[PDB]
Image (cartoon, coloured by chain):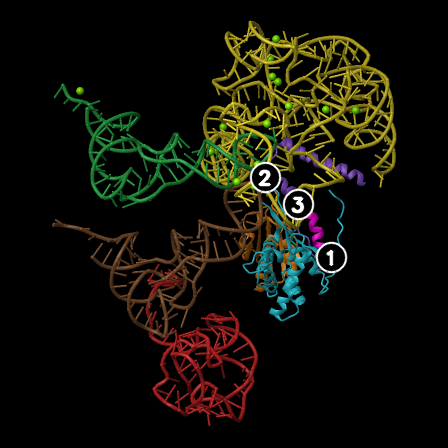
Chain colours: A purple, B cyan, C orange, D green, E brown, F yellow, G red
Amino acid sequence: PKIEVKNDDLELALKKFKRVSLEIRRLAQRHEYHLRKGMRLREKRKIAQKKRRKFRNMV
Amino acid sequence: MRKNRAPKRTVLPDPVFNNTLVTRIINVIMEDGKKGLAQRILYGAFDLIEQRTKEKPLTVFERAVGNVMPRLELRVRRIAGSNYQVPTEVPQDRKIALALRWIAMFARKRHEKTMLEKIANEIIDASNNTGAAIKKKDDTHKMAEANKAFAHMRW
Amino acid sequence: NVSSGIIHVSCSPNNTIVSASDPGGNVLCWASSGTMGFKGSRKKTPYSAGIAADKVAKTVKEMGMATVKLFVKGTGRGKDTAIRSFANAGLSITEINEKTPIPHNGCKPPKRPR
RNA sequence: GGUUCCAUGGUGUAGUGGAUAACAUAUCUCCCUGUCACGGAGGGGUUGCGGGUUCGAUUCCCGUUGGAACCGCCA
RNA sequence: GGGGAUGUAGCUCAACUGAUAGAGCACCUGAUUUGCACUCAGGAGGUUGAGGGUUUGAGACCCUUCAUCUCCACCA
RNA sequence: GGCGAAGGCGAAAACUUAGGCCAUUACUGACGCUUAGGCUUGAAAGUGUGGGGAGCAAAUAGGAUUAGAUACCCUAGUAGUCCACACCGUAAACGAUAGAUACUAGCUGUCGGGGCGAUCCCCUCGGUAGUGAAGUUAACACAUUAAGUAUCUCGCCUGGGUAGUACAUUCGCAAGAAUGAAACUCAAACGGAAUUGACGGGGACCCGCACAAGUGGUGGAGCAUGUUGCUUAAUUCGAC
RNA sequence: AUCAGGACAUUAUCAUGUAGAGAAUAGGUAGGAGCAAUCGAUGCAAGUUCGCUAGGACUUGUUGAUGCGAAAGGUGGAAUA
Ligand SMILES: [Mg+2]
Ligand SMILES: [Mg+2]
Ligand SMILES: [Mg+2]
Ligand SMILES: [Mg+2]
Ligand SMILES: [Mg+2]
Ligand SMILES: [Mg+2]
Ligand SMILES: [Mg+2]
Ligand SMILES: [Mg+2]
Ligand SMILES: [Mg+2]
Ligand SMILES: [Mg+2]
Ligand SMILES: [Mg+2]
Ligand SMILES: [Mg+2]
Ligand SMILES: [Mg+2]
Ligand SMILES: [Mg+2]
Ligand SMILES: [Mg+2]
Ligand SMILES: [Mg+2]
Ligand SMILES: [Mg+2]
Ligand SMILES: [Mg+2]
């Protein structure tokens, strides 16, 4: 997950790096705990439903 | 849970050296509701300060009290076990208040003679950064410096 | 004695590690929250991560490098305090690449404490 | 019948090479709680019997009780 | 018997081959707990075994004793 | 979101192979639905033999916490989790809703085939969802994928505890599975839905010397007064 | 037989080097009391010595005709060519 600094400013790098790390942290923390396959599908289905319903009202 | 900010009573400019702070410390050394007695004791100490330090009493008092005055305050915040402390910047009004409260408490415990000379020695002893009030200010400051890490989380 | 190099900064949820290394292997210096003097639970606080970065930044700057590739690691809490620590030290941060181990569904993770 | 060990507070156990006896539980008083348990503070309570040595015995010595542990074979 | 060690605070041990009397834990007070502890601050506690000499000076260097620790040989 | 009757199926490829949807000027001409008995499949755990074992972790050991902790936390850790061949045949195996057939407003999505030809969008035929009236229901709710109007067939139910227990029987190497009572006891049941409160170491909001910030006290001492206990011929009675 | 490595001895290598005080890094003794000048002054620049981060000596570069109060002056246990 390389992001170039562009050497024009520093903040901008961290403004993109905050996003990249958050999506990175989701899977990093997911492959930290063992749920049964049924429970694993439940959290996958749970996140999709949250994101969907949230996306409906900003569109 | 109150949503209301308390009012503040006037501090009054001092009646001699015209230095407000004298009235506050007078009220601090007040005991038994004696305005008179407290004034006499305190003013008498300035006559001894003249006799001893050969300098202006108001200047010595500001140099002692302003120097004893602390900067950081550690507020106790318990969650599960013991309390992790939080250093916060004290407002200016409260800043002066702890110094005066502290000056009197260590004055009424010295091995000296009549509290007149007792309090006189404490004020002259704090103008040179070597006393009992200094140690208290040093101790709370060192705890805050030790507890710099937990300053970001307050409540 | 080298101009460019790599600094791996691993941020575990319980501790942190900052390793300054040559562009390929062969670390030149290292520091950690334990070596600072913090012990027990305080080692996992962002302030400690910043403190560790400051000492290692100071040591390696006297050794004399300018361009730094920052291999950020871990999933702790002080993952950005050490990054900002280097920036106030003034080293030239060139890349902000992240290399926290991610699995592709390999190995079963431990059980959940409850 | 014979030989070794033990007897310390209310209960389980340490010490003492003569001058001195503690630990835990238990007990009592007070915080603690609607109340009680748990928790906190403080308080208290001791050498099996006898008989000698010593200025002085729980300790050292010889006997007498009680409780144990060992043995009591060859024909 | 021969060699090698040690003695510094209440309890262990650093020193430093000569110029500091120290570190840690026990004891005490302060911050802090539901407690119990952990943590944080301060403080004391020494003929540096004795004796003699070195050096301008010593606990140290050397000599000799006292005590304990180790060892390392043993046909009355 | 897709597929399969269910369990289930998600890196890529090859071989073998199952079912399904749409249009049929083709063909057979009732050959169809259900199914006691029977057969096949059937999550995970478990069994037997032989391999495999990185990670994790029942049993087990230790450190914590605790009044106690054989548990929740942490460090280790065997069987097991994996493969091949043999068994076991149970699950909240759930859409808690057997299969088949015909009919009954509508609206919004999404997927596949077909018709048009940039998609997008429109129509037709089906699968999978949401909302929704008549209708049904004790209510929650179902509502063209019915729990609605009706038909066929199979399986199952007859108060609660005893009890899925005991005996007999069948299967299984084993644990066990299937089948399955009674004596005795109760007036109801860890019955169903819904309502008003209370409560929550459930949330959201708002108040008071509540906490916080200060001041002066109490608990330690002497004394005054009241109470508990004890005593006494009585220590009159009540307030706890 | 050969190679490489460090053990410990060295042939042979001389700065090192840090009581106060003293102007001073005082390693101990310079025999002593002025001495060095192509047997080359003096100058400042670079590196190194080790550190008691003040200072030390040494080398290199400038490099040329008087330096050396580390002779005589200094204090000190230790001392000035
Ligand atoms: Mg875990
Ligand atoms: Mg009370
Ligand atoms: Mg016989
Ligand atoms: Mg299985
Ligand atoms: Mg155990
Ligand atoms: Mg483990
Ligand atoms: Mg097993
Ligand atoms: Mg069943
Ligand atoms: Mg509905
Ligand atoms: Mg019945
Ligand atoms: Mg049955
Ligand atoms: Mg029942
Ligand atoms: Mg209700
Ligand atoms: Mg308060
Ligand atoms: Mg009282
Ligand atoms: Mg009392
Ligand atoms: Mg009464
Ligand atoms: Mg009554």
The kind of residue tagged 1 is Val
Q: Which mark is residue C106?
A: 2
Q: Nearer the viewer, residue A4 or B76?
A: B76
Is any atom of residue C81 visible in this view?
yes
Figure quadrant of residue B134: bottom right
Q: Which SS type dominates the magenta stretch?
A: helix
SS for tag 3?
helix
Label 2 vs label 1: CA separation? 72 Å
Residue corresponding to mark 1: B11
Eyeballing the image, is F127 above or below E76? above
Instruction: Kindly identify the amino acid type of the residue bearing the numbered disc 3.
Output: Ile
Residue with the mark numbered 3: A24
Q: Is residue F29 left or right of residue B31?
A: right
Whether the residue carrying mark 3 lies under 8 Å from ligand 1 is answered with no
Whether residue C114 is visible here, answered yes or no, is no
> Image quarter for residue F115?
top right
In the picture, measured across the screen, residue C84 lies left or right of residue F132, that is: left
Up/down of G52 relative to F102, above or below: below
Q: Secondary structure at mark 1?
A: loop
Neighbourhood count class around disc 3 (C-alpha, 10 Å): few under 14, some 14–19, many 20 upward: some
Left or right: E59, with F73 as reference point:
left
Q: Residue at x 72, y 52 (%)?
A: A15
- Give SS at disc 2: loop
